[PDB]
Length: 121
Length: 116
Ligand SMILES: [Ca+2]
Ligand SMILES: [Ca+2]
Ligand SMILES: [Ca+2]
Ligand SMILES: [Ca+2]
Ligand SMILES: [Ca+2]
Ligand SMILES: [Ca+2]
Ligand SMILES: [Ca+2]
Image 1: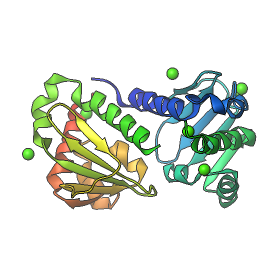
Image 2 (image 1 turned 90 degrees about the vertical axis):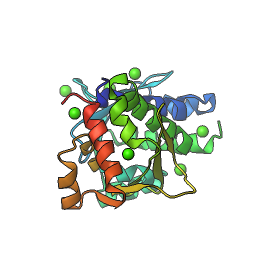
Image 3 (image 1 turned 180 degrees about the vertical axis):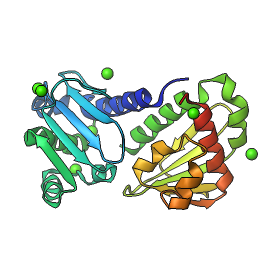
């Protein structure tokens, strides 16, 4: 029997790495996140998601004893809305997404996801 | 993006439910069943097709499901406890269409797959 939570964090990590780190065209967009710790608190879920950005991959953890550079709090249904910085600004303004710490981290993350969709690799 | 998401969900479900040979008789209750999962707020459906070897997940399905479940994402981790599924249906947190036995068997299997 494999516990559920580590399987979920491993799955998210695999998805993020294939989507964001596989293409070398995105290197300059990923550089903006190097060394950043982004904590994601999904409302209604009892656990946190912590994304640690390095040069060759992002690591996803279910716990983090240290400091996060940016912390985002939102319901899961906000994720398909994070299409670009415009939508991100509207979500912050409406209170659908709450940001603590460095707002630039989540702006750079959303910008990277936007470019990852643009880039056909 | 959709085939990457479904492949990830398929891998998660198979490692969680299909890895242990001890669960074979519990999985047999779902053989040939199709379970559609509509996560509220998301534009796409998740379709789970149960076979003896594995569960297959698809993002698109030209067909009917034996059972369809509709809920917000936060209700999804509450689906590994068979005794609370009735409470979720009663509270309206989980809406069920079609054959209720399919989701009951799925939750019973998910409960047996995990130490509390
Ligand atoms: Ca890792
Ligand atoms: Ca501190
Ligand atoms: Ca830091
Ligand atoms: Ca976009
Ligand atoms: Ca791409
Ligand atoms: Ca049966
Ligand atoms: Ca259990």
